Image (tube, rainbow, N blue to C red):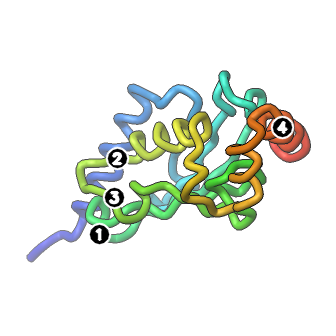
Amino acid sequence: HHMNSMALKRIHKELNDLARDPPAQCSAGPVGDDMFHWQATIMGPNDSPYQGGVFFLTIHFPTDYPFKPPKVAFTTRIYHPNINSNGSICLDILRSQWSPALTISKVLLSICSLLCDPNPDDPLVPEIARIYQTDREKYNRIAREWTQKYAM
């Protein structure tokens, strides 16, 4: 017979790799004994208006990982064009551009990259995209305000 544990082995591998080479601002791991449900924490990137913030996420790996992406959501509020009040993240690799070559460390690094470099032309929060496009000084000030309001 078969053992059906290859997703679990992949997730374990990815967890061990994460400990040895952490994406710098980030921690992540299983909530308790369930390897398919993780929590994560992202410290606001230093050259970003989220500096000083601590943002919590949930990660749910599918049973057929790595052949489908993990489902990742923010649980902390953030002022960003691509992350909505439900914590949903608009990031290509979590949708059409997922590859089984990717890993949770790559996903966390890409979220951090998104925090630094929003994609305002593919928004989940259209006002925040508008402010980003038209008045970056205002965007950074409000993003700092919200970091202090919700993420510190």
Picture mark count = 4
Q: Nearer the viewer, residue 24 or 147?
A: 147
Q: In this view of the protein, which residue sits in the foreground, 12 or 135? A: 135
Give whichever of discs 4 and 1 has the lower sequence position: 1
Label 4 vs 3, first from the N-terminus: 3
Q: Report the amino acid beneath label 4.
A: Lys
Determine whether label 2 and label 1 are within 8 Å by CB: no
Query: What type is the residue that disc 3 sits on?
Result: Gln
User: Between tags 2 and 4, which lies in front?
Assistant: 4
Q: CA distance from mark 4 to mark 1?
A: 43 Å
- The residue labelled by disc 1 is 64
Q: Residue furthest front?
A: 134
Tell me the kind of residue under disc 2: Thr
CB-based contact (under 8 Å), mark 4 and mark 3? no
Earlier in the chain: of badge 3 and badge 1, it is: 1
Report which residue position mark 2 lands on: 103
